[PDB]
Image: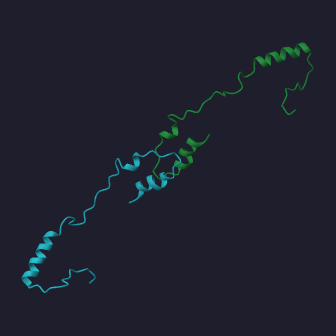
Chain colours: A green, B cyan
Protein backbone atom coordinates (compact mmCIF):
# COMPACT_ATOMS: atom_id res chain seq x y z
CA UNK A 1 0.00 0.00 0.00
CA UNK A 2 1.81 3.08 -1.29
CA UNK A 3 -0.97 5.44 -2.31
CA UNK A 4 -1.02 8.87 -0.69
CA UNK A 5 -4.22 9.07 1.36
CA UNK A 6 -6.27 11.97 2.60
CA UNK A 7 -5.29 12.66 6.21
CA UNK A 8 -7.40 14.40 8.83
CA UNK A 9 -4.41 15.94 10.60
CA UNK A 10 -6.50 17.59 13.30
CA UNK A 11 -10.06 17.08 14.48
CA UNK A 12 -12.19 13.96 14.87
CA UNK A 13 -15.40 14.01 12.82
CA UNK A 14 -18.37 11.77 13.42
CA UNK A 15 -19.33 9.34 10.65
CA UNK A 16 -21.93 11.79 9.32
CA UNK A 17 -19.43 14.66 9.20
CA UNK A 18 -16.95 12.39 7.45
CA UNK A 19 -19.61 11.38 4.92
CA UNK A 20 -20.59 14.99 4.23
CA UNK A 21 -16.93 15.96 3.86
CA UNK A 22 -16.06 13.13 1.48
CA UNK A 23 -19.16 13.65 -0.65
CA UNK A 24 -18.31 17.33 -1.01
CA UNK A 25 -14.66 16.63 -1.84
CA UNK A 26 -15.64 14.03 -4.43
CA UNK A 27 -18.08 16.46 -6.02
CA UNK A 28 -15.20 18.95 -6.05
CA UNK A 29 -12.93 16.41 -7.73
CA UNK A 30 -11.24 17.59 -10.88
CA UNK A 31 -13.47 15.63 -13.24
CA UNK A 32 -11.95 13.09 -15.62
CA UNK A 33 -8.39 12.42 -14.56
CA UNK A 34 -6.43 13.34 -17.70
CA UNK A 35 -7.26 14.01 -21.39
CA UNK A 36 -6.21 10.54 -22.55
CA UNK A 37 -8.17 11.09 -25.78
CA UNK A 38 -5.63 13.74 -26.88
CA UNK A 39 -4.25 12.80 -30.30
CA UNK A 40 -1.12 13.77 -32.20
CA UNK A 41 -1.76 16.19 -35.07
CA UNK A 42 1.40 17.88 -36.36
CA UNK A 43 -0.34 19.78 -39.19
CA UNK A 44 0.85 23.38 -39.32
CA UNK A 45 3.07 23.03 -36.26
CA UNK A 46 4.90 26.33 -35.53
CA UNK A 47 8.38 24.80 -36.03
CA UNK A 48 7.51 24.15 -39.68
CA UNK A 49 6.84 27.85 -40.23
CA UNK A 50 10.35 29.01 -39.27
CA UNK A 51 12.97 29.96 -41.81
CA UNK A 52 16.03 27.76 -41.35
CA UNK A 53 19.36 28.36 -42.99
CA UNK A 54 20.20 25.44 -45.24
CA UNK A 55 23.12 24.68 -42.89
CA UNK A 56 21.24 25.43 -39.63
CA UNK A 57 21.86 23.04 -36.72
CA UNK A 58 18.32 23.78 -35.54
CA UNK A 59 17.22 21.54 -38.42
CA UNK A 60 18.52 18.68 -36.27
CA UNK A 61 17.90 19.87 -32.74
CA UNK A 62 14.60 21.74 -33.27
CA UNK A 63 12.79 20.75 -36.49
CA UNK A 64 13.72 17.07 -36.70
CA UNK A 65 13.43 16.45 -32.97
CA UNK A 66 10.00 18.04 -32.86
CA UNK A 67 8.75 15.88 -35.70
CA UNK A 68 10.31 12.69 -34.35
CA UNK A 69 9.75 12.97 -30.61
CA UNK A 70 6.89 10.74 -29.52
CA UNK B 1 57.86 27.59 -71.79
CA UNK B 2 55.53 24.72 -70.97
CA UNK B 3 52.68 25.10 -73.44
CA UNK B 4 51.87 22.03 -75.49
CA UNK B 5 52.68 23.11 -79.05
CA UNK B 6 51.37 21.84 -82.34
CA UNK B 7 53.87 19.40 -83.80
CA UNK B 8 54.28 18.40 -87.44
CA UNK B 9 55.51 14.87 -86.80
CA UNK B 10 55.96 13.93 -90.47
CA UNK B 11 56.37 16.16 -93.50
CA UNK B 12 58.16 19.45 -94.12
CA UNK B 13 55.68 22.02 -95.44
CA UNK B 14 56.75 25.06 -97.37
CA UNK B 15 55.87 28.34 -95.59
CA UNK B 16 52.86 28.80 -97.89
CA UNK B 17 51.57 25.39 -96.85
CA UNK B 18 52.25 26.06 -93.18
CA UNK B 19 50.25 29.27 -93.53
CA UNK B 20 47.33 27.52 -95.23
CA UNK B 21 47.35 24.80 -92.56
CA UNK B 22 47.47 27.20 -89.63
CA UNK B 23 44.83 29.53 -91.08
CA UNK B 24 42.45 26.61 -91.60
CA UNK B 25 43.09 25.16 -88.14
CA UNK B 26 42.61 28.58 -86.54
CA UNK B 27 39.30 28.96 -88.36
CA UNK B 28 38.23 25.51 -87.17
CA UNK B 29 39.19 26.36 -83.59
CA UNK B 30 36.11 27.92 -82.05
CA UNK B 31 33.41 27.77 -79.43
CA UNK B 32 34.48 28.73 -75.90
CA UNK B 33 36.38 31.87 -76.89
CA UNK B 34 37.24 33.81 -73.73
CA UNK B 35 36.42 31.98 -70.42
CA UNK B 36 33.04 33.51 -69.66
CA UNK B 37 31.34 32.49 -66.40
CA UNK B 38 27.92 30.86 -66.23
CA UNK B 39 26.11 32.84 -63.53
CA UNK B 40 24.85 30.84 -60.55
CA UNK B 41 21.05 30.52 -60.45
CA UNK B 42 19.74 27.87 -58.04
CA UNK B 43 16.04 28.66 -58.59
CA UNK B 44 14.05 25.46 -59.08
CA UNK B 45 17.06 23.16 -58.75
CA UNK B 46 16.21 19.42 -58.91
CA UNK B 47 17.44 18.70 -55.35
CA UNK B 48 14.79 21.07 -53.99
CA UNK B 49 12.00 19.06 -55.64
CA UNK B 50 12.81 15.79 -53.86
CA UNK B 51 10.96 14.51 -50.83
CA UNK B 52 13.35 13.93 -47.94
CA UNK B 53 12.47 12.10 -44.77
CA UNK B 54 12.84 14.47 -41.81
CA UNK B 55 15.83 12.37 -40.69
CA UNK B 56 17.31 11.73 -44.16
CA UNK B 57 21.12 11.92 -44.19
CA UNK B 58 20.79 13.13 -47.77
CA UNK B 59 19.61 16.42 -46.26
CA UNK B 60 23.26 16.89 -45.33
CA UNK B 61 25.13 15.11 -48.09
CA UNK B 62 22.89 16.03 -51.06
CA UNK B 63 20.60 18.99 -50.32
CA UNK B 64 22.84 21.14 -48.14
CA UNK B 65 26.01 20.38 -50.07
CA UNK B 66 24.31 21.18 -53.38
CA UNK B 67 23.19 24.55 -52.01
CA UNK B 68 26.49 25.40 -50.34
CA UNK B 69 29.00 24.13 -52.90
CA UNK B 70 30.56 27.01 -54.77
Residue found 78% across the figure and 19% down from its top: A26
Where's residue B62, x and y in %? 45, 54
Quarter of the figure with residue B9? bottom left
Left or right: residue B33 versus residue A47 is left
Picture quarter with the N terminus of chain A: top right
Where's residue A6, x and y in %? 85, 26
Picture layout, residue B29 above or below residue A25: below
Query: A19 and B25: which one is in front?
Result: B25
Q: How many marks?
A: 0
Where's residue A15, x and y in %? 91, 15
Outermost residue, left direction?
B16
Picture layout, residue A38 above or below residue A12: below
Outermost residue, top direction?
A16
Left or right: residue B39 versus residue A20 is left
Residue found 52% across the figure and 51% down from its top: A57
Quarter of the figure with residue B32? bottom left
Outermost residue, front direction?
B10
Left or right: residue A22 versus residue B69 is right
Residue found 11% across the figure and 75% down from its top: B23
Picture layout, residue B17 above or below residue A57: below
Residue found 57% across the figure and 45% down from its top: A65
Query: A45 and A22: which one is in front?
Result: A45
Picture quarter with the C terminus of chain A: top right
Quarter of the figure with residue A42? top right
Query: B42 and A14: which one is in front?
Result: B42
Where's residue B60, x and y in %? 48, 54
Outermost residue, bottom direction?
B12
Amino acid sequence: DHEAHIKVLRGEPTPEEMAALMAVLASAGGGPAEPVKKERNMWGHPVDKLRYSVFSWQRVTLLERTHMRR
